[PDB]
Image: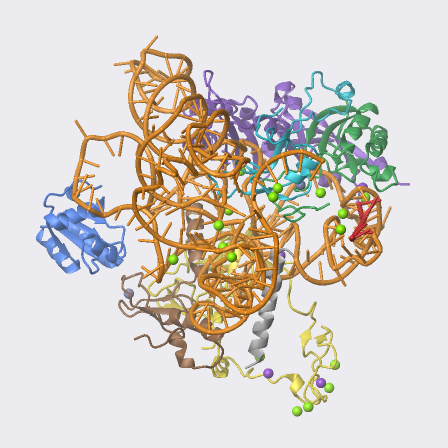
Chain colours: A brown, B yellow, C cyan, D purple, F green, G blue, H red, I orange
Amino acid sequence: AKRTKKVGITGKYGVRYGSSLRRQVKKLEIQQHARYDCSFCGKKTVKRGAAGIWTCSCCKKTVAGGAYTVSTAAAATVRSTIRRLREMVEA
Amino acid sequence: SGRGAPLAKVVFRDPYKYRLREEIFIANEGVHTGQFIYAGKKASLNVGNVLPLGSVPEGTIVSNVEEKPGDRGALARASGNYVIIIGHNPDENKTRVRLPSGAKKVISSDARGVIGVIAGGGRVDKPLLKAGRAFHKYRLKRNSWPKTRGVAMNPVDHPHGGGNHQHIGKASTISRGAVSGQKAGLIAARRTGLLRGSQKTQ
Amino acid sequence: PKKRASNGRNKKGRGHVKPVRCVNCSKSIPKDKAIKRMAIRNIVEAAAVRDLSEASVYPEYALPKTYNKLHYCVSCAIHARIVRVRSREDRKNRAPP
Amino acid sequence: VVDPFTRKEWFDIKAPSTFENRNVGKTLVNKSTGLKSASDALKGRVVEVCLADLQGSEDHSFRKIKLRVDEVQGKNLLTNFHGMDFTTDKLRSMVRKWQTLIEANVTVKTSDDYVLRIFAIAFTRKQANQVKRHSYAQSSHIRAIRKVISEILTKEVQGSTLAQLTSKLIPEVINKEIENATKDIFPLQNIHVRKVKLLKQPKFDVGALMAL
Amino acid sequence: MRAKWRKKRTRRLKRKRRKVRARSK
Amino acid sequence: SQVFGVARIYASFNDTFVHVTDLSGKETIARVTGGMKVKADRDESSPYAAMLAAQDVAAKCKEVGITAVHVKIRATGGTRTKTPGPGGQAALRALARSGLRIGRIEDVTPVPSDSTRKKGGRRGRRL
Amino acid sequence: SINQKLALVIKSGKYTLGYKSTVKSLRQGKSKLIIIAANTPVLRKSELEYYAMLSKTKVYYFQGGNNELGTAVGKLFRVGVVSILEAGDSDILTTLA
RNA sequence: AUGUUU
RNA sequence: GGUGAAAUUCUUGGAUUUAUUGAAGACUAACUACUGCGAAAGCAUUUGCCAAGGACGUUUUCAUUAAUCAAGAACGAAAGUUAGGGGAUCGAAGAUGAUCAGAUACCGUCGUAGUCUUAACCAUAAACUAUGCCGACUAGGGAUCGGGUGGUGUUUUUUUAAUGACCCACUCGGCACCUUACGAGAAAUCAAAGUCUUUGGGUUCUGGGGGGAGUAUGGUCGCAAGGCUGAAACUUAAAGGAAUUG
Ligand SMILES: [K+]
Ligand SMILES: [K+]
Ligand SMILES: [K+]
Ligand SMILES: [K+]
Ligand SMILES: [Mg+2]
Ligand SMILES: [Mg+2]
Ligand SMILES: [Mg+2]
Ligand SMILES: [Mg+2]
Ligand SMILES: [Mg+2]
Ligand SMILES: [Mg+2]
Ligand SMILES: [Mg+2]
Ligand SMILES: [Mg+2]
Ligand SMILES: [Mg+2]
Ligand SMILES: [Mg+2]
Ligand SMILES: [Mg+2]
Ligand SMILES: [Mg+2]
Ligand SMILES: [Mg+2]
Ligand SMILES: [Mg+2]
Ligand SMILES: [Mg+2]
Ligand SMILES: [Mg+2]
Ligand SMILES: [Mg+2]
Ligand SMILES: [Mg+2]
Ligand SMILES: [Mg+2]
Ligand SMILES: [Zn+2]
Ligand SMILES: [Zn+2]
């Protein structure tokens, strides 16, 4: 069954710290404990070590990422921007 | 430990002696193990490569930027931070860059930076939620926590101490020319109060 | 009742038309509703076409025109008499004079 | 009680080596002194002269030309091409209702080093027997016409120097090239190269400047 | 009174009533 | 066989500038405005003040050595009016009639590509 | 498209899925074409290219990853490399390059 | 430009 | 500078104006229309990529798979909320100048939130054509957008021919428009608001004099603002619609 209506993973915090703080924590906790797709082996086996470290349990490859998600929007934008700059300067 | 951004141990060959040289870089986002990092004037514009600031086009995002050529990294080292190349001055060779704080700086065009953004970004977006988590954060940085308010002390302990109510008593904005023991509060504050309006003055 | 067969605007098949600002008072009007007049006045009418042609260093100068599309709100157009109140049947006439 | 014009001297602006006429006019500046040379206050000035007064013929009354002073040579400010724009009168006269306006712009480097942005314009037109009263294009015609114009300007630049492009702009041969390459898409009455913009200059190269 | 301002005044009244009912228990 | 300046008439409402400069525009000669030649605070844009200011500008111009002027006339433009104020025509007529020669009149009013949301609010000035 | 040709091969012809069977077919000389997923590791890609040049076999680089390649060949699992043994009635072997 | 009420 | 006229304001520390530059954010003029697309809200610089869509054409295919839809879902202007970024402009609040009898309004000068963007909410507008959707039929006409067909067609060149643009005629679909109304309507007006006392093609939603009142209460959604649902007591002979003459 569904055990909690809305607190989800933040049920461990009980009634403490405030609902809005528990929500802000819930979003990033789900992000940080999710399993992500390995961009090298194609499996859904990438999990976080410490903040910013994302290791695939298969193929043993670890990539630097965001503190709570494998890729921040800033870093994806920076990746696309640097790709564009490289391609423009080289051609 | 004590750092938000992860480090990358990058092994180069020693160009003058047969051996390996391990280096401790701050990992940029997207850098992975087994990746070939290229460092030098002629390295390609790829995330994780180390380039001189002059060799990158305007708008490039770099990290661990040298303030002076060869100081091995001073700027945009914290998690999620980066420097933006906003232009070059080829004569009197220099690069104008935007620092994380919003400041514009002119650096030698020979100073190096790492392509990309420091990994670990978004870290401060999670509420600590707990004195215990603040405790464990500063346990690996320094003894600066917890902080007793000076207004909760006695006059002997702090400028803000004393009084039959807790209150500063005098303006908390302290002159830049004040001396040690006086510089508690808002040192050399240009202004106070809730920031309303836009930043980046001209 | 409904005063105008379509509306006091020109919008059928659209839903939303981006607004323009009245040149006289800055009121926002939908572009299709605004009263639009073109002005092609001579850059020098000024009673002084002859004087300017005399002072000109160029023979047959062909002095230019100033072009300006003016957008009036209904209130401003009526007040400045770019447009006038018409009879119930005269309103049903879309030709210019 | 100073009369600032008692200490100002005149220089003659010699714009081209190529337009028709070297002398475009005069400009005044403070007499050179201890810590403020007159050449420093000159050598940056841009003048905007009508191409009709540059070429001598009144069929260039639009298309003003910007010329910036590159060097001071003995009371003679030798300038070079700095940009071209149409006049507001001509542009507003060309922009009319009941027709489709088509604009293209490209950024391209001249053969030597000059980075330019070229703004070409064109307008649809009625045919001779046309009864329909607006002659609008279908925006696929507009895309194709803009592609053709962009290619034409990109290949006109990159094969000419700044001087040769400036000498191509006066006959308006690029207008006719666009007309001939677009006449099978849409009639395109009023093709023009409405603007040339200097975005970045090369190293000064006084050797190349000194041709006038 | 204008219907818009009647609605606004009524909404302000409703807010005050909610606040009074909240303070009571 | 002459000396050309630029007339740079800025004919707003509430004022008219007659500002003659060298061909470059950096060096200026005899910038006179209608508020200099009238003291009523409401005749600053009037054609009479414009004519007096243009006459003063023409005198200083052919005292400095300017004989002809290329004319650049403008309104406030930007986002505000786009229509040349009442003083511009009078200023240019006075410049023509004060002995100066005239060349290449052009309207250089700043016109946006639909920028800069206009002042006044969406209901405009309610007078 | 390439996915259509692949589906037709899977339905009609003969094929092997996976690195080991693909290398076996290449060394036996009964591979007509090998399709390598985009995210296949470069070492394995180079080994397959060497085997394919030794066997004079054509190589097609599938633009998707192993997930996309498995989906294209109609399997619910990842496929890093496909080997075509017999095209059946499908023009995948001639509509290349 | 301002000019309330019956 | 600004206005009807002023004043606040800036200004010989050179304001305003001029020229040459640079930065930032927003916006996308003119072209722009009784023109287009989208379920609506909406959508207007170029190019690239990604999927989608209507109409048309079709001697392609399936063969009733359909229409409308309580419950239930997706989207949903602006304002507003939360958290980052951004913050040029304009600008709820606020501050001030002036009018004024008062003017904490209109007008002037600033100016916070907001305006912009990302990630989430909110779910409301005169969200309007105040006109549900599907189907059929009943006048005439000329324009116009998209597609198609035909022509001794005009112009455009490649070498026959050709697309393209245009002209003419037809056609399907669309935004509309003009005239007349057999007909409808209280009328204004309406090709649908017609084919309705000669009253039945299918189907969903809504209303039952004016207030009290979209109020109270309960439920539910929402962070909140609020949304959805929603009375009664009591009161009242009119309220209201269209049109006519003053
Ligand atoms: K404390
Ligand atoms: K104290
Ligand atoms: K004035
Ligand atoms: K702002
Ligand atoms: Mg603290
Ligand atoms: Mg104590
Ligand atoms: Mg003390
Ligand atoms: Mg003290
Ligand atoms: Mg105490
Ligand atoms: Mg009425
Ligand atoms: Mg609407
Ligand atoms: Mg009025
Ligand atoms: Mg009033
Ligand atoms: Mg009475
Ligand atoms: Mg004034
Ligand atoms: Mg545009
Ligand atoms: Mg269109
Ligand atoms: Mg429902
Ligand atoms: Mg919105
Ligand atoms: Mg409603
Ligand atoms: Mg309704
Ligand atoms: Mg009732
Ligand atoms: Mg009535
Ligand atoms: Zn892996
Ligand atoms: Zn108006």
Q: Nearer the viewer, residue C79 or G23?
A: C79
Report whether residue F7 is seen. Answer: yes
Where residue A4 sits, quadrant-wise, is bottom left
Numbered-mark total? 0
Q: Looking at the image, is B78 positioned above or below residue F89?
A: below
Position of the N terminus of chain B, as image quadrant, is bottom left
Q: Looking at the image, is E7 positioned above or below residue D187?
A: below
Q: Position of residue A3 (x, y in %)?
A: 34, 77
Where residue B11 sits, quadrant-wise, is bottom left
Q: Is residue F114 left or right of residue F90?
A: left
Q: Position of residue F49 (x, y in %)?
A: 84, 34
Position of the C terminus of chain B, as image quadrant, is bottom right
Q: Looking at the image, is A1 positioned above or below residue G53?
A: below
Q: Position of residue I81 (x, y in %)?
A: 55, 65
Q: Looking at the image, is B140 positioned above or below residue I222?
A: below
Q: Nearer the viewer, residue D66 or C42?
A: C42
Q: Nearer the viewer, residue A80 or F10?
A: F10
Where residue I132 sits, quadrant-wise, is top left
Q: Residue at x 59, y 60 (%)?
A: E7
Q: Residue at x 14, y 51 (%)?
A: G10
Report whether residue A67 is seen. Answer: no
Q: Nearer the viewer, residue B199 or G11?
A: G11
Q: Quadrant of ligand 12?
A: top right
Q: Position of residue B81 (x, y in %)?
A: 50, 64
